[PDB]
Amino acid sequence: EQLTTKDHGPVFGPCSQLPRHTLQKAKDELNEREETREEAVRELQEMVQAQAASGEELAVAVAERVQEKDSGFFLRFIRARKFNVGRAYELLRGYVNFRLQYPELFDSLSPEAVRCTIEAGYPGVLSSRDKYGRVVMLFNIENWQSQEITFDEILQAYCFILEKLLENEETQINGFCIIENFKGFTMQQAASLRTSDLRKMVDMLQDSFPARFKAIHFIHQPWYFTTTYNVVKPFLKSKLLERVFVHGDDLSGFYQEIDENILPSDFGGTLPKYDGKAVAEQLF
Ligand SMILES: CC1=C(/C=C/C(C)=C/C=C\C(C)=C\C=O)C(C)(C)CCC1
Image (cartoon, rainbow, N blue to C red; front, side, top):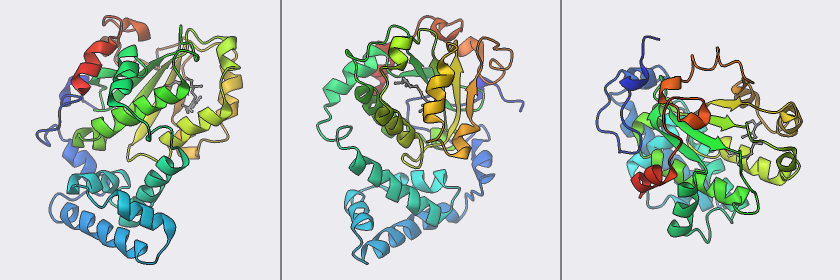
């Protein structure tokens, strides 16, 4: 506690320093500034290739994909698995595995086509971190039309925005936090949701990307959100479930976690209605 939303560095821009006591926070996930980081990455690659030297298909796939990756890359996986090399490696396995199970989201990807979606505002990204230093990602389902923008395109956007934002060590340590504006959620939309797609999302969220998803928030959901929650509820591991938060309209427990002050009008905040063009530009 005793940490203001401001205390944390900029979203988007590669980190510059470790101040703002976040470095200590990481140390509290068993991090050591002194001798660990350097070796861990080594150990991982030593493990990556070792397990690929067995001839096993996956461990090999990994070895190929990561054959040309800076040390900061591998650190992303170390940081996310609490500095457990083994666990860290497993995240790398599942990480590659995801791309394999889901070709469409990474194969014909066009840097141009993606920008279109991100400018469209799906998803959104708060230009600011919450009081914890977490990238607050946004989605506003109101007026969404699945025929115009595919649930896939929206996920591909997530993937890009993750690959990018994860270049920032601050983000790596504070994690993410998603806001879900289900105010415009229609029954026509609820039934238009492929369970196959929902798993795709869930998968992204679980043991796929080297991120710390700390909280999912839902707001203004209809009385039938329970129907859609119960469909996904089986997929979510305990850790993630305990992090899903449905506030309804009583934000007297919501605004403590997320400061109304940094939120666009779209999500009950003071700021101007979310701008996709602004965000997208900073991306590229
Ligand atoms: C309830 C539940 C989910 C379902 C989200 C809804 C049903 C998705 C619909 C629109 C999309 C594209 C929004 C993207 O931000 C998750 C995320 C699987 C896991 C968290 C708990």
